[PDB]
Image (cartoon, each protein chain N blue to C red):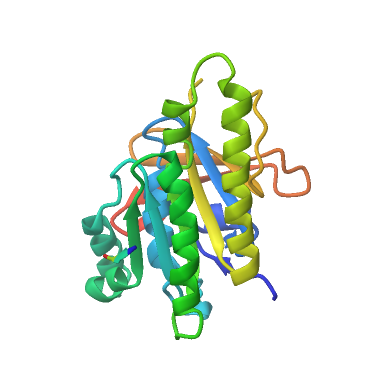
Length: 227
Length: 4
């Protein structure tokens, strides 16, 4: 299947990404608390529902929320300010809260059932969010021996997510809170996000020498994100 | 999962 691309709402970030985030890929955004990772997730969960000529994929959303940070009111705001019906946009976002990392892993299997259910509808799943990908793994796998064990479990979880992305033509979007680099990562594309002044945010592609080497700049607004 |  040919890949698809979901606009982020920022022309600058879209150019950095070659048009938007890709299906059949895992895009990881990482950065400090408050950098805007979850704002980008909320924005994508609306943008994906737009028709293709407007930068969406007419798609539904699966959202695995590990920090109780999904906000339907934020979806509503973004949708209304983009000309969309907030209640209809919310209808096509299917959210589960992950209690711990083992539940988070099982939820990926449950996600496949929802993906299959919607595959032949007019709004197949096109976006799968895991926010936060790493928070439960960080709290549970800690101390001597944990680096190897945590990395193995996280790699297996990411492999399961890669399979859904690739088998069902879905863009997987995951968030990871960092601080202040030595660990392996298996996402397709890694985007470092940081906060500038007020509502301004700066994005850079990490370890992607074949792709744009500049930086995108965008603002958090009532439309989600915009230039 | 549950619809929002």
